[PDB]
Amino acid sequence: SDLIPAPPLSKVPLQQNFQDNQFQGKWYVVGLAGNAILREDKDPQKMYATIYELKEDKSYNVTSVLFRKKKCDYAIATFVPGSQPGEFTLGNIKSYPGLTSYLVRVVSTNYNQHAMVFFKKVSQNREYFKITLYGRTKELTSELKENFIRFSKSLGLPENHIVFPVPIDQCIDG
Ligand SMILES: O=C(N[C@@H](CO)C(=O)O)c1cccc(O)c1O
Ligand SMILES: O=C(O)c1cccc(O)c1O
Ligand SMILES: O=C(O)c1cccc(O)c1O
Ligand SMILES: [Fe+3]
Image (cartoon, rainbow, N blue to C red; front, side, top):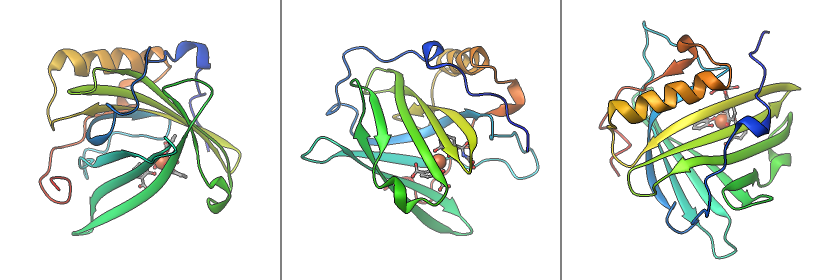
């Protein structure tokens, strides 16, 4: 098992003055990069969506909806506010076997069109990280997509570790 090393947190910017209420709602995954993400031209990555909902204790209810094997698949997690706004840790980490750490950092966002989010986890002692380019719609300008490519590269990732999921209508239009 071989992995590109997780970048130092100093190389991962934090979105300033993070507004947690404005980050709520559905985001489409228009770009996906990481040391475990690989471009697969035979069976290309389908677009999925992630929905953020503020609980009254100001932690997030996070639901991901994916189109897999002709059905809609639902992954639930809780994001608990971390050291500073825009940073999060994972709730009920014990319910995930082999998972020792999980970090979420909102790198950049304008809340109503786009967002870039950095994730880092240690699972079975292996360090994984990913950057998601979130779009409020299924499509984003080639400029924003290029910014995402340059940011992914700055964290050590080559082009074959950066994918742009193909837009779909099943499951993610709810
Ligand atoms: O790369 C990741 N996971 C792969 C499995 O190890 C994957 O299949 O996407 C990954 C990295 C950081 C944070 C994550 O939630 C995550 O799924
Ligand atoms: O369980 C998944 O496949 C999944 C879906 C959306 C986001 C993730 O991080 C996941 O691990
Ligand atoms: O974000 C998650 O729900 C999650 C938790 C543990 C392991 C994963 O890969 C995840 O995507
Ligand atoms: Fe994950």
